[PDB]
Image 1: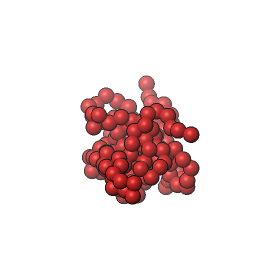
Image 2: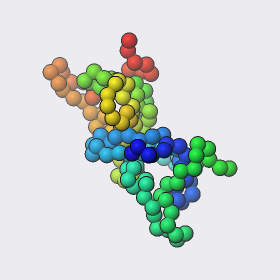
Image 3: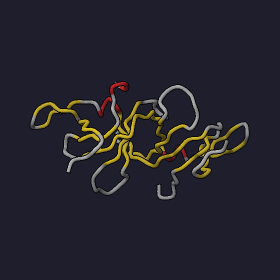
Length: 77
Length: 78
């Protein structure tokens, strides 16, 4: 909770997202991350996700990687 | 319901005001939720999320049927 840093993150699949901050999910009283996608696709641009899941390390074909990696306040080209 | 949702300032039926920033998709459940911030002093996380269908429900206290959250524009009262 306390050490979470809102800002731009790169999901392990390659796309960038802007984490606006943490929030309390009313139905379960759990801490979620509120974020918007920084790429074009169809559907709702904003999403939420449990902080504990967002912070997980995930196994991939490219080896262990953070599910979402913090990269600052700007995104690359 | 999504199409009729208007982000902005809402007055919860209990008297306090909140700022709904917009709609969001909860990643785990794929449910549609409202992202909002409280506009009054209290301890805790200022932002919250709540299912759109619950946010849109009507409630009946000791004064008759009324919106759980009533839209009042983009500003809060004096």
